[PDB]
Image (tube, rainbow over all chains, first blue to last red; front, side, top):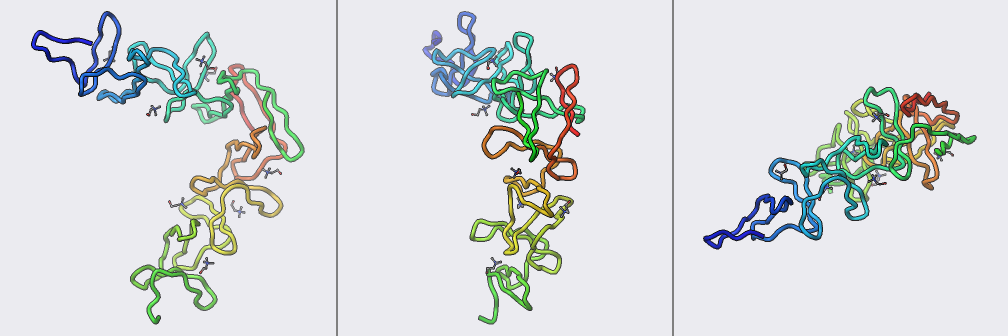
Length: 133
Length: 127
Ligand SMILES: C[N+](C)(C)CCO
Ligand SMILES: C[N+](C)(C)CCO
Ligand SMILES: C[N+](C)(C)CCO
Ligand SMILES: C[N+](C)(C)CCO
Ligand SMILES: C[N+](C)(C)CCO
Ligand SMILES: C[N+](C)(C)CCO
Ligand SMILES: C[N+](C)(C)CCO
Ligand SMILES: C[N+](C)(C)CCO
């Protein structure tokens, strides 16, 4: 936290203390373990120490990705040169789902662990039940 | 008594739904008090069977209630979105036990022998 000469402190704004970003509410306390869709329309999240999230974060048993300046991203993002799909709506990594290509031609499959499958092996049964491996 | 209000009513053997004014509903969905959706055509007859409403397809049971999920028609399955009740097509739907997927074709019919072509970058195309 910061306190000025007049004794006032920052309220409802972002502040970078010693090279780390934090957010203080309209009461002067920093958000901790909390989201906030900033005035800039981007979503942010702060952990136990109130530090602004960067990169991947497991939040409430789900995974989100944050750019280097704090905003949550959606769509495809590569990590360890392998792709992941983040729900364009809610923002959490998808898994075991068929996400349709951008050229409407087809689909991209993401395995139960979230990693895109670029060697998907299909197995169909008599009634047509697809089973992906 | 002589002025039907907020109630369904069978007239000339046909179901109609009466709004608060005593006028039939016409070209309107109307989630009833039983948790089901109902549609009435231009005459105000209660929808039954299949109905292409706003270029989207729907299926209602012989009682008027709109169906969702897997409905079998002419020994060929079709899947109805549990969300808005419309007919899914060229999409994959999870099997009821989360063990696999079923593919619904452009025309809406379940494919029993879908063929897959996996391109270099992993992209999948269905036929
Ligand atoms: C952060 N990752 C998306 C790479 C892990 C979830 O599997
Ligand atoms: C909190 N901000 C996103 C405005 C700073 C990072 O550049
Ligand atoms: C939808 N989000 C995951 C971005 C946060 C809402 O609290
Ligand atoms: C999709 N269904 C499982 C209902 C058809 C195969 O029996
Ligand atoms: C399934 N129908 C034959 C009733 C029409 C929708 O394509
Ligand atoms: C079959 N309906 C539900 C439309 C009649 C009940 O009054
Ligand atoms: C989902 N329904 C189409 C049944 C409601 C009207 O929007
Ligand atoms: C990121 N994409 C899924 C669009 C490329 C496939 O490798």
